Image (cartoon, rainbow, N blue to C red):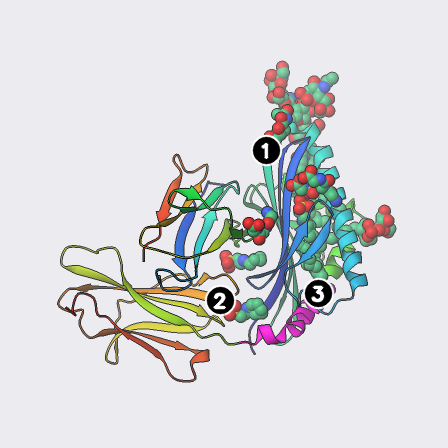
């Protein structure tokens, strides 16, 4: 089965409010095979306090994962989602903007 | 309601060689994860207060036992045959088993399997049926299960066709206050990637609504703007939904455009947001 590259979509639960509790989400879907590295980044650094769904697949059998973490944004801090796959030469990044 | 509901357990097995493999299983009520599997202790992880679904602790520990025997036997057979034919490693098996409840109450069982992401076989009524792709391996496994494996096929039929619908409905009733809740969305506006010089991309974010049906449009007055593009309805943490609606417009034609949101929780009072942008000093 032809390798499929992940689609990465990054979005927040609430409007960005500097100094307010909020949730950052990263939805990664449509990839095959199942081995993958997803991380949520705060200032280029991997966040450890994270939650993810158990591995699941659609009907075309490609896989998908939801990641999220609770966080409080400020002008200084930027957040991201980084993904590494076999179909990825370099770890792809997607950045979150207010 | 007229809507189909479904419950599935899904498994993913990777076999790297004859001495190393790993796996993952979970339970899903529609697109909501309701169960996990702790693989060291071979037990069910109940994610919600209502996840036992009105089953007794006795039936549940017996299901855990049944799943443990099934995992043991599955890996033992696959390894016996793949160790001799060791040119197959590394390979990945996907399993999706479960049931759908159609609008009139008719149950429908499901047991599909894929190999390296390709349909391998399925369980149609009472027969293991290979897929057109590959055959051979598919035909082999299918004959194996049709004639060389005891009450296994009997138990699978009983599980997807009687135990599963009963557990589906017990789950829905056990969590009725969660199942039938309404959660109001909140909306906001942003700019998107520039579509070109002299052009803007307007974005309306709608987040935190449950249930899933929602209406979102860019408007000028009562003219719905035909260019509105809807994204995928994406999942939030804790069971709510998220949605983007975007619109490309020349600057000079952006004034007067608004985002309108209709949802079951809103008691007729729609959410309206006017694009301000660089219009206001
Ligand atoms: C409770 C729930 C219920 C349980 C659910 C689970 C049940 C269902 C799934 C389980 C079953 C799945 C279906 C299986 C059906 C089977 O029926 C089976 C029958 O198919 C054939 O089987 C045979 C097995 O024997 C294979 O033959 C072996 O293949 C091996 C790998 O290829 C080796 O081949 C060699 O490899 C080498 C690599 O170095 C070289 O390349 C060689 O090449 C040649 O070398 C030459 C050297 O000079 C020349 O160069 C020449 O030119 C060149 O060609 C090549 N040699 C060839 C081509 O001949 C072996 O060869 C050796 C070797 O080297 O090891 C030779 C040794 O000398 C010999 N020693 C001696 C002393 O002599 C040794 C030994 O004797 C053998 O016995 C093996 O060890 O074997 C050979 O035997 C055939 O491929 C294969 O097609 N099909 C399979 O798919 C098996 C794997 C399936 C695994 C399952 C995968 C997914 C499962 C999905 C399950 C779905 C779950 C559903 C859930 C249901 C819910 C209830
Ligand atoms: C993530 C966690 C999910 C949690 C949600 C709960 C799940 C909810 C509630 C229900 C959904 C069901 C899902 C939809 C379906 C998937 C089930 C899985 C895929 C397949 C299982 C079947 C196995 C293949 C075992 C059958 C073989 C035995 C053998 C015959 C019967 C005797 O058992 P045994 O104990 O072995 O007893 C046997 O008796 C036999 C005598 O006849 C003997 O042959 C045996 O030796 C043995 O003694
Ligand atoms: C089997 O796979 C495991 C996992 O990579 C590896 O550590 C082990 O060495 C493998 N065995 C081999 C290659 O003989
Ligand atoms: N891989 C085991 C697991 O923990 N799965 C689901 C989950 O919720 N992970 C969140 C976490 O612990 O980071
Ligand atoms: N066939 C793979 C499998 O099911 N192994 C049993 C198990 O418990 N795996 C957990 C793990 O080691 O990942
Ligand atoms: N019921 C336990 C099982 O079948 N496999 C898990 C195990 O034995 N060890 C866990 C591991 O090695 O990761
Ligand atoms: O492509 S698709 O329509 O989204 C496939 C549906 N996924 C479900 C199948 C197994 C349980 C998880 C939810
Ligand atoms: O590797 S592992 O964590 O043991 C995968 C477990 N899968 C099981 C989940 C519940 C019943 C179907 C099989
Ligand atoms: O909004 S919705 O997610 O499409 C509602 C239907 N899906 C199910 C989700 C989990 C509980 C049972 C209902």
- State which region is magenta: B161-181
| Residue that badge 3 annotates | B52
Residue linked to disc 1 = B90
Residue at 66% x, 66% y is B49
Tell whether B220 sits left or right of B245.
left
**What residue do we see at 64% from left, 72% from top?**
B175
Name the element at disc 3: loop
Q: Quadrant of ligand 6?
A: top right
**CB at disc 1 and ligand 3 closer than 8 Å:** no
For mark 2, name the chain. Answer: B
Q: In the rendered structure, does residue B238 fall within the stretch colored magenta?
A: no
Determine whether, in the image, residue B40 is placed left or right of residue B102.
right
Q: Distance of mark 2 from mark 3, alpha carbons? A: 22 Å
Q: How many residues crowd mark 1 within 10 Å: few (<14), some (14–19), many (20+)? A: some
* Location of mark 2 (residue): B240
Q: In this view, does B51 lie above or below B11?
A: below
The image's mark for residue B134 is: none
Quadrant of the rendered structure where residue A87 is?
A: top left
Pair 2/1: label in front: 2
């Amino acid at each position: 089965a032809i390798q499929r590259t992940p689609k990465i979509q990054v979005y927040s639960r609430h409007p960005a409010e500097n100094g307010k509790s909020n949730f950052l989400n990263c939805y990664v879907s449509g990839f095959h095979p199942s081995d993958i590295e997803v991380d949520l980044l705060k200032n280029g650094e991997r966040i450890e306090k994270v939650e993810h769904s158990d591995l699941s697949f659609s009907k075309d059998w490609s896989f998908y994962l939801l990641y999220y973490t609770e966080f409080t944004p400020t002008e200084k801090d930027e957040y991201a989602c980084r993904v590494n796959h076999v179909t990825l030469s370099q770890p792809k990044i997607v950045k979150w903007d207010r | 309601s007229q809507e189909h509901v479904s419950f599935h357990v899904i498994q993913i097995f990777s076999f790297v060689n004859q001495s190393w493999a790993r796996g993952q299983g979970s339970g899903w009520l529609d697109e909501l994860q309701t169960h996990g599997w702790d693989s060291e202790s071979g037990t069910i992880i109940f994610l919600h207060q209502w996840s036992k679904g009105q089953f007794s602790n006795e039936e549940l520990s017996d299901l855990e036992l049944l799943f443990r025997f099934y995992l043991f036997g599955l890996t033992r057979e696959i390894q016996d045959h793949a160790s001799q034919d060791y040119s197959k490693y590394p390979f990945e098996v996907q399993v999706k088993a479960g049931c759908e409840l159609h609008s009139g109450g008719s149950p429908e069982g499901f047991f599909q399997v894929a190999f390296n992401g390709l349909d391998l076989l399925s369980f149609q009524q009472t027969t293991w049926v290979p897929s057109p792709g590959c055959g051979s391996l598919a035909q082999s496994v299918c004959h194996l299960l049709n004639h060389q494996y005891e009450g296994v096929t009997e138990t699978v039929y009983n599980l997807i066709r009687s135990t599963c619908p009963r557990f589906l409905l017990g789950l829905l009733d056990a969590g009725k206050m969660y199942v039938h809740r309404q959660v109001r969305p909140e909306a906001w506006l942003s700019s998107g990637p520039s579509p070109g010089p002299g052009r803007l991309q307007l974005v309306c974010h709608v987040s935190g609504f449950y249930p899933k049906p929602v209406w979102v449009m860019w408007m000028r007055g009562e003219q719905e703007q035909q260019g509105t593009q809807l994204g995928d309805i994406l999942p939030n943490a804790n069971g709510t939904w998220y949605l983007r609606a975007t619109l490309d417009v020349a600057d000079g034609e952006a004034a007067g455009l608004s985002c309108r949101v209709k949802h079951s929780s809103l008691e007729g009072q729609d959410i309206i947001l006017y694009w301000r942008g660089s219009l206001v000093p």
